[PDB]
Image (tube, coloured by chain):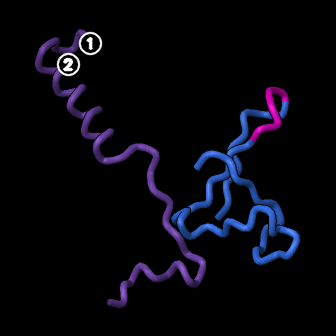
Chain colours: A purple, B blue
Amino acid sequence: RDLICAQKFKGLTVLPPLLTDEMIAQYTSALLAGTITSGWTF
Amino acid sequence: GVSVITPGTNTSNQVAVLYQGVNCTEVPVAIHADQLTPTWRVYSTGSNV
């Protein structure tokens, strides 16, 4: 029940990134769709 | 951490407050009890959440 991420109590926190994993996946999907359907033209 | 989100004092004096890493069923809601100081901060507001 004791987690290694209980470093918050010593003042050490982690900030979440601006782009989520879903948004990075959507950027990657847009890159793949453009590369497959349009070549280098996009 | 407390983060203050402002559009700039040239535009408006309205701010939005981000209490970093905590839930807001857990944020102290002493809005009209701020003069009694149960908080490290003095300011307290009750805007849209």
- Nearest the viewer among B7 and A27 is B7
Q: CA distance from mark 2 to mark 1?
A: 6 Å
Please name the residue that numbered disc 2 is placed on: A34
Disc 1 residue type? Phe
Disc 2 residue type? Gly
Q: Is residue A36 above or below residue A14?
A: above
Q: Residue furthest bottom?
A: A2
- Residue at 68%, 65% in the rendered image: B29
Question: Can residue B20 be spotted in the picture?
Answer: yes
* Quadrant, the C terminus of chain A: top left
Q: Residue furthest right?
A: B35
Residue B11 percent coordinates (x, y): 80, 27
* Sooner in the amino-acid sequence: mark 2 or mark 1: 2
**B48 on left or right of A14:** right
Q: Which residues are magenta?
A: B10-14
Q: Residue furthest left?
A: A36
Please tell me whether mark 2 sits on a helix, a strand or a loop: helix
- Residue at 79%, 68% in the rendered image: B41
- Residue at 71%, 50% in the rendered image: B4
Q: Are the two marked residues, 2 and 1, in contact with CB atoms closer than 8 angstroms?
A: yes
Q: Is residue A36 above or below residue B1?
A: above
A11 magenta-colored: no
Q: Main SS of the magenta segment? A: loop
Please name the residue that numbered disc 1 is placed on: A42
